[PDB]
Amino acid sequence: ANRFTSNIKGLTQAARNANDGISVAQTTEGALSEINNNLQRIRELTVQAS
Amino acid sequence: TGTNSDSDLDSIQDEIKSRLDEIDRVSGQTQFNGVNVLAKDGSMKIQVGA
């Protein structure tokens, strides 16, 4: 029972820590959306100025 | 025509010279968007694709 309790607490803590990764990746994709849109805009007036 | 006198020829020459001067004027001075389309030789290309 002691081993199972320790294992369950560890699994719960790891499961809680896991969502940190998806939060970080969501922040990163939100940040790089700016790079995507700005690069597309640069391509836009690059086509314009060609 | 041979019936024209010398003075008539000189008078016609005035109109000829006026037309030549205005031709040179319209050729040199015309421009579009700051570009002398007719005054100087060149080759300008329009990009029509991404």
Image (cartoon, coloured by chain):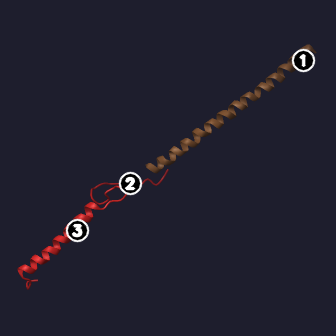
Crowdedness near tag 3: few (<14), some (14–19) or many (≥20) residues, C-alpha within 10 Å: few
Q: Which disc, if any, is residue A5?
A: 1
Q: Where is residue B10 shown, x and y percent of the image? A: 9, 76
Instruction: Say whether disc 2 or disc 3 marks the residue closer to the N-terminus.
Output: 3
The residue positioned 23% from the left and 68% from the top of the image is B22
Crowdedness near tag 1: few (<14), some (14–19) or many (≥20) residues, C-alpha within 10 Å: few
Tell me: B41 left or right of B48: left
For label 3, the SS is helix
Distance between the alpha carbons at the discs numbered 2 and 1 = 76 Å
Identify the residue position indicated by label 3 in the image. B22
- Which residue reaches farthest left? B6
Tell me: A31 left or right of A45: right
The residue positioned 44% from the left and 49% from the top of the image is A49
Q: Are marks 2 and 1 in one subunit?
A: no
- Subunit ID for the residue under disc 2: B
For label 2, the SS is loop
Quarter holding residue B32: bottom left
Distance between the alpha carbons at the discs numbered 1 and 3 = 102 Å
Identify the residue position indicated by label 2 in the image. B45
Q: Amino acid at mark 1?
A: Thr
